[PDB]
Length: 266
Image 1 (cartoon, helix red, strand yellow):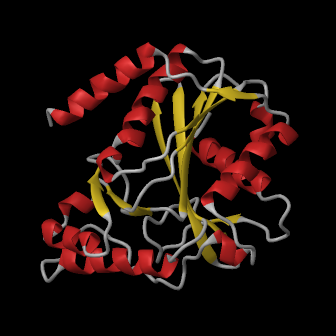
Image 2 (cartoon, one colour; image 1 turned 120 degrees about the vertical axis):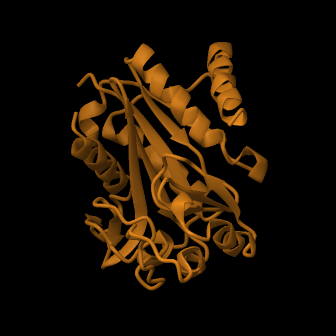
């Protein structure tokens, strides 16, 4: 349970992506924090990173027969395609989507435990609402996962996990407000075009725009990404966590640039 990690301080790193040119910034920090949590395993890092209109593509997506034609579907709605060679299935980010990561040191275990740690955190964050939050895969959502979060059968969040040595990075993309039906239709179009008539052995989701929704709608309570962030930070103190500003030491920036340089030469 989330409250079980309260022994460690939570370092906060709010770093928005305000320009499509910095779209890779969050993923670069993920790498940095995964190493740091291994060197400094006496704390938890809460990396908050909402972004401008972006569609993050993963390993399977880039194998689409007509990829470039598909990316056009993304560009036509004013979103920027970002490719992550080892990332999961296409997910959407924008002003109405909250993305963040919990970088945890393995010092208190399993892949499931990690996901369940996030589920508990989310539930705790919205404990003031009666609507119970469930987890199970919503197969017809984009980027379906065993731990998709939903309320009344509708998915409002997708989770992801990456690990390195004794460090774990659990991430989540939460639909807070905005045009969720549009985000969904965009990805459906992406896969339709990407597959064209060529097809593929890879099982890509068959997106259903009516199966996903914003949390502000599911909770019948208008809220912005900033509102959730605040609610989330407040829930920490109540649960028993002590927090502090994560300081970007020169060393951290240095490591960031190594990962950035690596990417650039690619």
